[PDB]
Image (cartoon, rainbow over all chains, first blue to last red; front, side, top):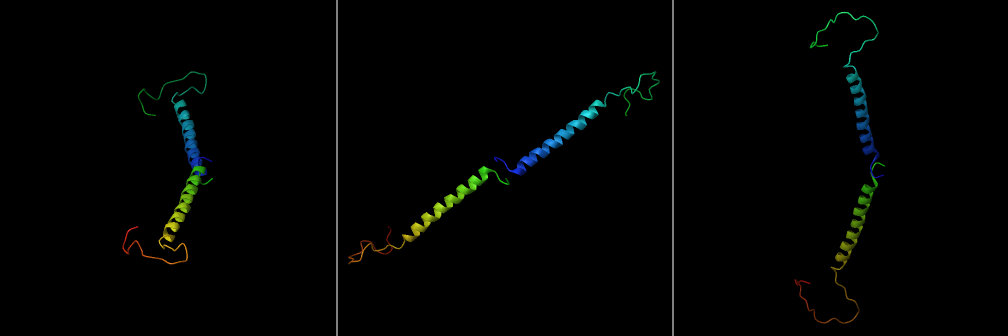
Length: 53
Length: 53
């Protein structure tokens, strides 16, 4: 009881936002490595280095 | 828990200071009527009107 319920609430809210932001950012980072879904013969790239995807 | 214990302690302390300050002001104000301690004969006033005491 050294702080109000509100102050704890506000601090807990900010934390939950941060937790969320991390998890999304982690997923996007993981997607920077475009991986093969299967083993097989890959063909031609429809995309050249330096292109925007 | 809408306020902390410190906040309440501080409000309680300010209130109690107020009680003490009213009592002292009441006392000062009662003393502006200077009263005879006993029945008897009074002589000369050693102090005039308009004097400082």
